[PDB]
Image: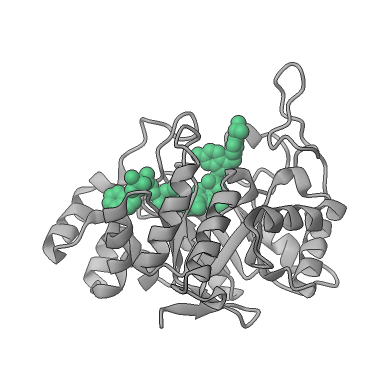
Amino acid sequence: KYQCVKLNDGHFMPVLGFGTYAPAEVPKSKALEAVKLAIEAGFHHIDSAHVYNNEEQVGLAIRSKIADGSVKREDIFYTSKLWSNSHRPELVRPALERSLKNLQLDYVDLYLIHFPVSVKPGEEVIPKDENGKILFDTVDLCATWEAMEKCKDAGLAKSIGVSNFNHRLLEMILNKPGLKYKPVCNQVECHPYFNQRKLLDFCKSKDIVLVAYSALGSHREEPWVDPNSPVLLEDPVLCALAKKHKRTPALIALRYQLQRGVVVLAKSYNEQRIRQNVQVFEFQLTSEEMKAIDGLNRNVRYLTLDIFAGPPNYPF
Ligand SMILES: NC(=O)c1ccc[n+]([C@@H]2O[C@H](COP(=O)([O-])OP(=O)(O)OC[C@H]3O[C@@H](n4cnc5c(N)ncnc54)[C@H](OP(=O)(O)O)[C@@H]3O)[C@@H](O)[C@H]2O)c1
Ligand SMILES: CC1=C(CC(=O)O)c2cc(F)ccc2/C1=C\c1ccc([S@](C)=O)cc1
């Protein structure tokens, strides 16, 4: 057994997920080893994406742990994400199918619209013209969503949701004429320096689960994250709580999200830290402790993805 939350489509999501994105100079071979270790350690939820260029490796890890008897498919919750070169409705299903072919899995547990800004179709994930300008596309995300809905009806994705959607964009889905399935989740950046209280409350009001990414304060990889940004795990309140509980500031940050009703992801490729992260289920924080962490909030967004800024659907 393991701790899960019931989603608004009746499916269940394990409340601690393993993040698999790593910076491009980390060999992709490391994702295979990391995901096996995560499963060994007790992660039952794995988070990936077409754009991470690791599905072949993450799929092999998963297949390997099923084929060797360590786990059944039904006790792995695997997430993929639809990349912005395949937002046009007729391209959605084929993108899910290529992900599944690369994974050698029959279905994904969850399939997300990765990012609301669309780019031109084709093999290149960031297509650019000869002058280096990103080739943006104009796509109605309500039509993208209908195509997602069909992928759920075909059984290829058990559940569907979104990522990096703001209030306006969620409403655009929620208020869609003929809407068949709400998003089960909105995966977004969330941590004690950016606690997303406002959007969290909105999502709760609509029974959408907020899935927190960069919950340990991000990979901090340039140029995507401003190296001047404060180091979350160096926070003195988190480090003092850690010290007090004989845990680590990472565990404190992760426990904070579980108690506030958020599903939390944690990436690590390091064997010790992978094992340590499942200890989030071994301790609890008091109301006073929780309030102290709410106090750390400071409007710090680490991951702007501002290479996609300009178009109206840029969410930040
Ligand atoms: N939907 C989206 O657009 C989106 C955006 C960003 C991320 N994500 C997903 O969310 C996942 C997590 O976000 P993310 O990678 O920014 O990083 P994140 O989990 O905040 O973690 C960042 C850093 O924490 C380190 N770490 C892990 N456990 C630790 C521990 N116990 N003590 C000290 N350090 C620890 C990792 O290094 P080691 O590997 O060496 O441990 C990693 O570099 C990604 O892999 C991806 O699946 C999705
Ligand atoms: C959407 C996305 C994210 C968020 C995530 O982890 O889900 C991400 C995070 C990073 F630190 C760097 C890139 C990405 C990214 C997509 C992406 C963009 C350009 C490239 S390069 C120019 O080919 C590769 C990937």
Identify the residue shown where x is 55% and y is 58%.
Answer: 187
Question: Can you tell which quarter of the image residue 100 is in?
Answer: bottom right
- Taking the image as shown, residue 240 lies to the left or right of residue 158, namely left
Q: Quadrant of the N terminus?
A: bottom left
Question: Can you tell which quarter of the image residue 276 is in?
Answer: bottom left
Vertical position of residue 109 compared to residue 265: above or below: below
- Taking the image as shown, residue 80 lies to the left or right of residue 297, namely right
Residue 310 rendering spot, x and y as whole percentages:
69, 34
Identify the residue shown where x is 85% and y is 69%.
Answer: 177
Total numbered labels: 0
Question: Can you tell which quarter of the image residue 136 is in?
Answer: top right
- Taking the image as shown, residue 288 lies to the left or right of residue 157, namely left
Residue 87 rendering spot, x and y as whole percentages:
78, 49
Front residue (pair 148, 241)? 148
Residue at the front extreme? 68
Residue 147 rendering spot, x and y as whole percentages:
82, 62
Q: Quadrant of the C terminus?
A: top right
Colouring method of the image: one colour
Vertical position of residue 117 compared to residue 246: above or below: above
Front residue (pair 218, 200)? 218
Front residue (pair 96, 292)? 96
Identify the residue shown where x is 59% and y is 71%.
Answer: 208
Residue 190 rendering spot, x and y as whole percentages:
44, 55
Residue 52 visible to the viewer: yes
Residue 284 visible to the viewer: no
Residue at the top extreme? 131
Front residue (pair 316, 136)? 136
